[PDB]
Length: 330
Image (cartoon, rainbow, N blue to C red; front, top):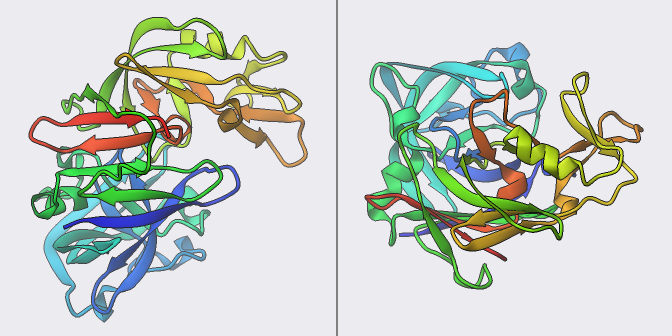
């Protein structure tokens, strides 16, 4: 089998992407944030505290003839941005882009933190990291990809995120029309549960490529590119007036600037992030200070190849027995 679904930016900045997902019988369609940095499929639901729902579409398990309570199971997750959610668990039929999994754990939110409530466009998350990170207790549950894998034509999914435009998540096949050149594959460590790999270096604008190993994760659920402070300083030093602002929480730059590109290495290959992809717009409405799309990872503990980086590439998440990542230009 295969599946193919369009993913759409939630706003004009590409802060996140939503993909429609069918849950239950008859289908209830929710728009989920596909997150290769986590491993829980959780939804706003009829069980979510009413004051914490503000415009989201909810899953109502009592209206699904295929929903079954997973008795005793609870979940609770905290994300790197400080947001969180928790609740109980149902199993139900879940379809993405024509690919159907029966018996998928659908984690129903009883509580969500304010950033989720405040984002009316995201009805939940669909985790695509390794199932060892799934938070369901006492019986850990598998991701949608893990459950689908054996039925897929090939044990892969691909992320093709758009810049200010829709893109595609495919399951089970590699669309050879969706990229240019060849796909360069690179090793993955699953030891932390992430799609963790090592970039071979970087360049700023037209500058020379610096060969240096940068371990990080491919994370569709993180908006920006978070890299070591040395790399980030080298980038922003090429932008007149750019500075790191403790009050804003990262590097800002004059909105009048034209930003240089940023290149990252994948083996001997190179992915170029155009400068425009690094512009996240005014820090507050009407400000002439703009927020940068490349930020330091120093306070995180891990480097994160988020959407800013991934949307410059066609990305293969290869879930074969030894997983690997593939990157192509597009």
